[PDB]
Image (cartoon, coloured by chain):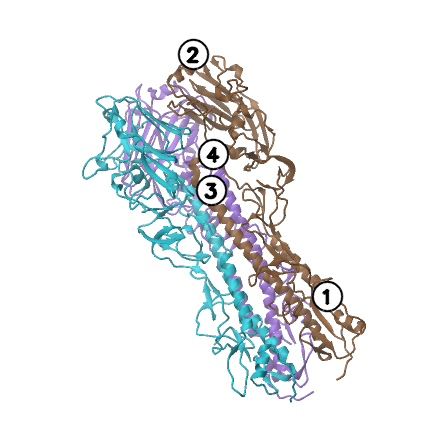
Chain colours: A cyan, B purple, C brown
Amino acid sequence: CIGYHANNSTEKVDTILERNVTVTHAKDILEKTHNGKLCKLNGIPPLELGDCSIAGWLLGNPECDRLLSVPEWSYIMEKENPRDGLCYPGSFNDYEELKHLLSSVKHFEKVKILPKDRWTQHTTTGGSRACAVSGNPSFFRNMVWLTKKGSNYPVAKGSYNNTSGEQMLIIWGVHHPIDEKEQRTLYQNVGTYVSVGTSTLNKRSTPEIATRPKVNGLGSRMEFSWTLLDMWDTINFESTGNLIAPEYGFKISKRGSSGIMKTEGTLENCETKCQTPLGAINTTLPFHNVHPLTIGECPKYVKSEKLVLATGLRNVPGLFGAIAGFIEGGWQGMVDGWYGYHHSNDQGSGYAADKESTQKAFDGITNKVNSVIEKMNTQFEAVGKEFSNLERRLENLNKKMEDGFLDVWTYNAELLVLMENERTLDFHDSNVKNLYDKVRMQLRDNVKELGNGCFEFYHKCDDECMNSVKNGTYDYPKYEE
Amino acid sequence: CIGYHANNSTEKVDTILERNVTVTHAKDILEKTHNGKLCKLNGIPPLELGDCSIAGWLLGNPECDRLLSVPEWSYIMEKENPRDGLCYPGSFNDYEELKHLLSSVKHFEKVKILPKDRWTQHTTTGGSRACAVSGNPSFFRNMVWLTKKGSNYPVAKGSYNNTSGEQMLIIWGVHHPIDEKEQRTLYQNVGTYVSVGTSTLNKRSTPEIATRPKVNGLGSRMEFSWTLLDMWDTINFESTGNLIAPEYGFKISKRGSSGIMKTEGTLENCETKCQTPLGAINTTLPFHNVHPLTIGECPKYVKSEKLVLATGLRNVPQGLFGAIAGFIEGGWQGMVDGWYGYHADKESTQKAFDGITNKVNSVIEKMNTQFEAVGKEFSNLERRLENLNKKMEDGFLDVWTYNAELLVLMENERTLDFHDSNVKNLYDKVRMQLRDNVKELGNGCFEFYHKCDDECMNSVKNGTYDYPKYEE
Amino acid sequence: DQICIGYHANNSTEKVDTILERNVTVTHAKDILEKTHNGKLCKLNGIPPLELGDCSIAGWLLGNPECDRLLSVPEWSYIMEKENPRDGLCYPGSFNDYEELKHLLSSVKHFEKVKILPKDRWTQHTTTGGSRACAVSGNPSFFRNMVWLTKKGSNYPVAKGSYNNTSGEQMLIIWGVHHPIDEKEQRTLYQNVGTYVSVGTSTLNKRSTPEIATRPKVNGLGSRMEFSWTLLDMWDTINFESTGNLIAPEYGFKISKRGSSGIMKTEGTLENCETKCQTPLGAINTTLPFHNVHPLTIGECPKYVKSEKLVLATGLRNVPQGLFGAIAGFIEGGWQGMVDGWYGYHHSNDQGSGYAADKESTQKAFDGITNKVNSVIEKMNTQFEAVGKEFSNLERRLENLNKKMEDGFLDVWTYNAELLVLMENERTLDFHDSNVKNLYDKVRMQLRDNVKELGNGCFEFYHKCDDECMNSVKNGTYDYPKYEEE
């Protein structure tokens, strides 16, 4: 008797042609588990900003004083709406761009470039209530609010030749008052400007005085801008009022660039190739469905709940008419493989598997499952991008495209599972119909072929004769009836 | 005798291996029909701008006075080149952005915020020939052209604390003259400015006086800008010349955001989940090819003329398993109660049918679809970006086409073979019952060596043949 | 006597993979991955590239004196720049909306330089302005295409100039603003101090103020020149007005276009060939749906894939000395001797041995495999893309959107094409298997009684089978007067 395997499994797969088909074995290829943790990424921690905006951190909001601050990070953790941004109300030009620039960094060191001391001739102690330090009027630790000394504001000049050996991120500001009287109180002079130069940059701001609602009590604003100073290049500042000067610069070496992850949680010291806001993924499968906003090298994100490839055969405690066919059902007793024999022997009967054809099948199904997994390229993407109020169009271009790929990968992967499942079942069917044939063509005359996949022997068949058939050696002196 | 179905069908499908193969049955999965109509979208009408640009509508070009104007729309209809834009020649900063913002809205109400009356101290009646109303010099209904009263233009001040309860779209302008003499005629003062403040916004414009060609007769221009005032926030205006002030604001609640559809036609009161400039699509198929510029939840747009899945079997009036068009040479037009039968096996016709039903569903149902706008807006200095969009839409067009074309072809070859296997299997089931008792003819017939009356014949269709026969 | 059904075999050591096996030697194959260029840069659809040598588009247009002798054609299809052209803005500066201008100029139907505000006519201002940095044979010179307006005597009267665009095509006009480092350099050149540079057309309205500021020296100058551009519509007028610091255009550029393409970063030079699809390593003259030459193509190209080989199997498994159990199955091995097709017979009898091929079923199979290989190739849409885009320093986010997307498509096409080859390979092998198991059956059902079926795909005849009887089996005509022996 020739037959196939069967077992306690209630696992269901779909094919193109049927659904809810119970199968002896399966392998889900949809990665759906995270570890609830935020982790290092390829051996390097994230910059952890707690509830500080990258603006507060850099500018040095006094409320950011005690942040981790590492010399090298791989992504950046912000909260969605950090609260601690520009304590003195304002704005920051090309902000989203700076954030992408800082998102990943090889080395990042703060360095004093235009020391506060040296601004003799101007007042340096300027501060506002809104940036309070223990109930005391303070200011952005990293900047210098240049105001009038006595009743005089001589041209302000300062420069810095970038010798540090790395490119440097320098940030500066312009103060916009609400009053041509606040303008005099601080700067005396009225028609002022704030000029800034390097080998590549040339900007000249004029203060824009204008009535404005109060934000943190102030109606005035401070407008910050930035630039990268190349190695061996010089930044030149010159103002006759309203300059907010940098005290420090930031050595910045990089790297490859990444992206910002919007989360509440905190670094937990683990390791992952692929980080998501719900947790890291340590996986090898080509698809996942944890969360869309990953950072690292991830499987393709898909809108699926399950992608269950069938590996084993139909479970029956096809296209070649054998499994669930002329061989009506499977054998739970044969457990040493997928296909096998049973024989009726007067010395006793039992369950022997064709290991030769179980090896073939198994090596094939292994290869199928590998094909599907290994041909899938994966590279380091950031996925979550930053956009301003005047970039909705662009933000949505990004969205239309991420949505575009979501649909491709879902349809393709869903169908891939279904087409390949119907193939597996049939492969198992063909393997059994072929075994049945191999056997049949050895016997012929000498057996009544029962039609349920059994052969009744017309002669005596002792164990040696039975192994002769599993051997592929049946031959063949018979005799009878 | 075992055999398969046949019929009058001349419908052709392709497979990977053959082409132009006549099949008993087929199901095109390419949606290629619209209804020539523009319709509501998910129960909500489009904003219908006629031939008004969003700039004219908002600014209130007098030529836009009588527009539909609904409190909630789902997309926006403009003509390609609306003609009625900035009747007083100029420009509008961040325009494309404003249009995307207005493309879809949950609630949109105009509201008077800085009433014309209250600008005592300045002249308010300013108008130009170019914005004529019945041959009469007029202006943007929604704005206030502040000029000098007598020979004096005192600082202009105005504010508005946004109490409406929704976020508000406020628009303002700056006038650039062509003459330091036009500049005096209207404003007296020469070194003027136009300052604007909110919690988040802070802008100060200076008028740029400069000789310029005439557009609508004027060489001067008006440069408009906008902002969204948050709830409970205040906008502050202050000018010493050249301000074009808003009279109204726009309450604007939204929503989800959509896009603008460039058409000539008009809303016809129907319903659709998916609108295209040629008409709406009421379809369930995963692919269409009506038009690239859809809005809504649509099938994937493909560069195909037909995607015809084969559902029935090869039509052979008079495969991979050697039965259909094989040892059983041709099909039977006589057997019409199913696909396979004797001389129909409803049991195996049901199996087959349920499978082919599932095939056709698999292909249709696994296709995700979501609300996309497709048609985007770009300025003259955004060609690079516009073309990024195009390279990508092109990118997806190629994927979906290649994939869907191949998908049809791979799955067709499978269907034919599936039918072939179904028949070779029927043939076998029967054969293994008879054996001895019949000469197997080889054309799929069995000649009985004994007598086979109707009960004996049902015994074979039953699966019950058994089996007292000793005849030769 | 005895007949025999079998399949083809040969000297081939070509391996394909399927979903189920790998490294499977096959009689025949067809790689569908285009991996060869011709090391050359070519015309594109019958039109040359603009060849900038080592000039930036800024230097070329502005007319850096170091760009004087460039090819300059009236119509190009893409643009060749070197990566870092060296000859850019010889007088240090910047150029607004530069990346956009480059995309605009990347492909052009007609492009003619035309003198619009002739140098002569700026009576009242000095015109000979030059700088050491733009030297011509050791002589202080300037951008050939611009006019450095400075003071005459000690007076700089308002500068005015206009041009009504009559040329008949849209015109690319470029202008500049000079930013000095000194309210003393500002006086030396322009006398006046609170100056401006105003520019107007039907659509454009810009007013620049010079920004004076201490700055590092670049090419020795601390001052800078900031250029901007616009397109003047037909019949429209550009108005210039300045009280100092204008760098005026002498020429305009008639520009008709077209369709727009992109810029190719290369070192080599145009070699006069032809290609529908150009890559920085060379042109591709191919018809296959995928290639892997280089990502930065321009023209109509196959989909770029991360593959080394995409080898479709066309012929059958090679077995010198499947899913239907025939090939590499009950018919244990293949025949190198049968060379007139894929499947055939061996018929042995007292008139000779000798292989026949079943040409009927070899034609079927071959027409099918031909169609397979065409399906895969022909259903692949292809259109004109540029692929290589231009982005400024403040556009890194955008540049990377482009990258994430090109990367997005790279993964789709690779996974899909890799898998496509594998799924279809397993289908071909099986298809050949089925063709043979079917031949074996067709034959078997004719014979029956009259032969011992050997089980290795041979039939030993129980009667005499002369050549006519053998052709009767290949014919499909075996019939059938035999009652030996028995």
The number of numbered badges drawn on the structure is 4
Residue at the image point whose x is 53% and y is 71% from the top: A358
Q: Callout 1, which amino acid?
A: Asp
Q: CA distance from mark 2 to mark 3?
A: 51 Å
* Element type at mark 2: loop
**Marks 1 and 3 close (CB-CB < 8 Å):** no
Q: Disc 4 or 3, which lies upstream in sequence?
A: 3
Q: Name the residue tied to disc 3.
A: B376
The x, y position of residue A354, in whole percent, is: 54, 75
Q: Name the residue tied to disc 1.
A: C358
Location of residue B129 with respect to A250 vertically, above or below: above
**Marks 2 and 4 close (CB-CB < 8 Å):** no
Q: Name the residue tied to disc 4.
A: B381
Location of residue B451 with respect to A130 vertically, above or below: below
Residue at the extreme left of the image, as rendered: A135
**Pointer 4 and pointer 3 on the same chain:** yes
Q: Nearer the viewer, residue A153 or C259?
A: A153
Q: Name the residue tied to disc 2.
A: C155
Q: Check disc 4: other Cα within 10 Å, few if <14, some if 14-19, many if 20+.
A: some
Q: CA distance from mark 4 to mark 3?
A: 15 Å
**Pointer 1 and pointer 3 on the same chain:** no
